[PDB]
């Protein structure tokens, strides 16, 4: 007489667009249209006085290969200057930025002329000078976070303003002072080529270009930081280091959301922002990157920083795995801390639905992807099938997936004995293919049952075929932290996939699992093995019972 425990449904977040998480973000550097005529060939009463930044110009990017600098190839193909630069190109001190998981800053053509003429051959667009982008892009959104009240990250920041002919800014070169081309971290008159510590005359170099520092309090899910401008330095001129911004943010999943506070009153472009969002990258949050957009739309800024290493104790926050049903091997998936969305090519596929398990079909061109996600009673995890389909109906890239939001380790129950029941998906292949399909038939379906003993840290599991007397697979595992690890097997006898060949006999199969939700009220895990022959790919989930 068991029954799912009652749980207060997960509280659903509705984020402003700018606050949605992505692998990266970019924006084009604004350039004033200097043309004297409009597209219909009539004289503008007034040549444009502005070129605005807007939320529609701030674009999500999602390239998996961070070696491919965004737009670098495009800029090279169209350039007539041959002057292509980017913030990681290593050609000056300020462009030597040693990050492993993140790229950020800018990529641009120093001098590029766009002239567009209409049918009548009248020029209605004329822009010139710097052409490029401000961006950040990260890879491997972190699945584990360091423990502690203060972890320091150091790095850079970069920016572009909007354009207004009324701007009278100081500290920027004629290449970008806001009148014809945006003021950017490219045109700012800062120290670019003298390393920290050097002395020019008796002037010590304190900093390079635009530097950032953050103090992350992982235990309290918060962080603060500072962004600095490090002025040009001579033997004739001591360096002026000024703080432009203070930052505060709160951490959710592997992301953070907050504000940037302008530190200098009365600046027409360096103003406050309520729209700061970024994330941790690297398996252990070795690095961080993000962006903000000022409230008066005067400025788009990005930043990136890394911690000194670790060799740090971490606590896992996320599981998101894909198991291939042909190689029976596993690979990581991008996830930001929401197990109910699948992220593909920057598109978020919502996995929830009205049914116990729900199928989703989405053209993420050019691939028609379909995912079957379970289950409606699992609030902090999902698992299911995922494949590309072509035709009516051949199938391609067939696989399994599992995602979960780990229970905090200090919220793991301290004892003792509880029951967990759920279902699973799997594929055992030796000769013929034997599948398991998730369902809600607690009686005689593809059942999963776990005895969990928090006292002596043990998980024991049974996984059944439909109309199954004894289990097809059992699991013996050990609870360590907020997850478990152990072995899946079958009886010493093995089990019939069908007479012509022996039962599938499996032993010492490596199984990884997690505890999910506020108080470990859900568990899930996977295993896979490739043998010639006798192979298997399986994912499973279950909910804690009461009574």
Image (cartoon, rainbow, N blue to C red):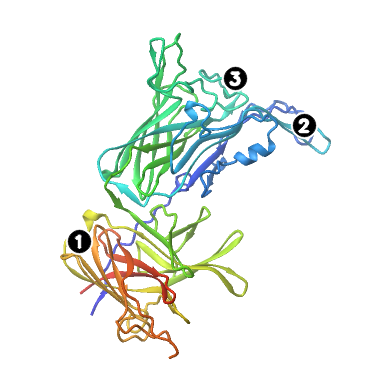
Q: Which residue is mark 3?
A: 174
Q: CA distance from mark 2 to mark 3?
A: 24 Å
Furthest-right residue in this view = 120
User: Badge 1 is on which residue?
Assistant: 413
Residue 251, x across and y down, in percent: 34, 45
Classify mark 1: helix, strand or loop.
Answer: loop
Q: Are marks 1 and 2 in contact (CB under 8 Å)?
A: no
Residue 403 appears in which quarter of the rendering?
bottom left
Q: Nearer the viewer, residue 256 or 84?
A: 84
Q: Position of residue 337 (x, y in %)?
A: 38, 54
If you read the primary sequence from the N terminus, does the residue marked by circle 1 or circle 2 appear first? 2
Q: Residue 157: percent from the left, percent from the top? A: 45, 32
Q: Of marks 2 and 3, which one's residue comes earlier in the chain?
A: 2
Name which residue lies at 24% across and 77% down. 2
What's the CA distance linking mark 1 and mark 2? 71 Å
Residue lying farthest to the front in this orientation = 532
Q: Nearer the viewer, residue 195 or 154?
A: 195
Q: Quadrant of residue 408?
A: bottom left
Q: Nearer the viewer, mark 1 or mark 2?
A: 1
- Which dot marks residue 123? 2
How busy is the neighbourhood of tag 2: few (under 14 within 10 Å), some, or many (20 plus)? some
| Mark 1 residue crowding within 10 angstroms, few (<14) / some (14–19) / many (20+) | some
Q: CA distance from mark 3 to mark 1?
A: 63 Å
Give the secondary structure at mark 3: loop
Q: Horizontal placement of 71 versus 403: left or right?
A: right
Query: In terms of sequence position, does the residue under pointer 3 or pointer 1 come before the other?
Result: 3
Q: Residues within 10 Å of mark 3 (few under 14, many from 20)?
A: some
Residue 217 percent location from the top left of the image: 28, 40
Residue at 78%, 31% (x, y): give it. 42
- Is residue 16 toward the left or the right of residue 217 in the image? right
From the viewer's perspective, tell me whether residue 446 is left or right of residue 35.
left
């Amino acid at each position: 007489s068991y029954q799912d425990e009652e749980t207060k449904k997960k509280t659903k977040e509705e984020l402003d667009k700018l606050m949605e998480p992505t692998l990266g973000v970019e924006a084009k550097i604004p350039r004033r249209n200097r043309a004297l005529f409009d597209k219909e060939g009539n004289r503008k009463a007034t040549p444009d006085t502005t070129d605005e930044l807007s939320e529609a110009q701030i674009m999500a990017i999602w390239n998996e290969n961070i070696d491919e600098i965004p737009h670098l190839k495009e800029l090279n193909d169209k350039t007539t200057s041959g002057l292509i630069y980017h913030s990681h190109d290593g050609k000056q001190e300020d462009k030597k930025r040693n990050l492993q998981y993140v790229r950020s800053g800018y990529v641009f053509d120093e001098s590029y002329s766009e002239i567009v003429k209409n049918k009548n051959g009248v020029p209605y667009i004329f822009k010139n000078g710097i052409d490029g982008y401000i961006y950040y892009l990260g890879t491997s959104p972190s699945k584990e976070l360091p423990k502690g009240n203060k972890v320091t990250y150091k790095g850079t920041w970069d920016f572009t303003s909007d354009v207004k002919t009324s701007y009278e800014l100081s500290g920027f070169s004629d290449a970008g002072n806001g009148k014809n081309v945006a003021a950017t971290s490219i045109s700012d008159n800062v120290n670019r080529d003298h390393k920290v510590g050097e002395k020019l005359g008796d002037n010590e170099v304190k900093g390079v270009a635009h530097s950032s520092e953050f103090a992350v309090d992982f235990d309290n899910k918060k962080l603060t930081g500072s962004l600095y401008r490090n002025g040009y330095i001579n033997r004739n001129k001591a360096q002026e280091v000024t703080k432009r911004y203070s930052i505060e943010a709160d951490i959710t999943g592997n992301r953070f959301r907050g504000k940037a506070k302008a530190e200098k009153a009365g600046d027409p472009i360096f103003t406050d922002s309520n729209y700061l969002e970024g994330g941790f990258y690297g398996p252990k949050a070795e690095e961080m990157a993000g962006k903000f957009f000022t409230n008066n739309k005067s400025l788009f800024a990005v930043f990136a920083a890394k911690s000194e290493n670790g060799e740090t104790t971490t606590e896992r926050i996320i599981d998101a795995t894909k198991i291939d049903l042909t190689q029976f091997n596993a690979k990581e998936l991008n996830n930001f801390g929401d197990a109910s969305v699948l992220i593909i090519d920057g598109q978020k596929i919502d996995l929830a639905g009205v049914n116990f398990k729900n199928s989703k079909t989405v053209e993420i061109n050019g691939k028609t992807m379909v995912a079957v996600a379970c289950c409606s009673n699992l609030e902090y995890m999902k698992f299911g099938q995922l494949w590309q389909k072509e035709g009516k109906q051949q199938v391609k890239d067939n696989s399994l997936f599992l995602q979960g939001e780990r229970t905090a380790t200090d919220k793991m129950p301290a004892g003792g004995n509880y029951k967990y029941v759920g279902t699973w998906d799997a594929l055992v292949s030796k000769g013929t293919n034997w599948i398991a399909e998730a369902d809600n038939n607690r009686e005689s379906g593809y059942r999963t049952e776990f005895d969990v003993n928090f006292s002596d840290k043990k998980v024991n599991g049974k996984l059944f075929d439909k109309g199954g007397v004894n289990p097809v697979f059992t699991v013996d595992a050990t609870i360590n932290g907020n997850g478990f690890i152990g072995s899946a097997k079958t009886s010493d006898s093995g089990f019939a996939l069908d007479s012509q060949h022996g039962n599938a006999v499996f032993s010492d199969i490596k199984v990884n699992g997690g505890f999910y939700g506020p108080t470990a009220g859900e568990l899930g895990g996977q295993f896979h093995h490739k043998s010639d022959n006798g192979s298997v790919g399986a994912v499973f989930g279950a909910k804690r019972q009461i009574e």
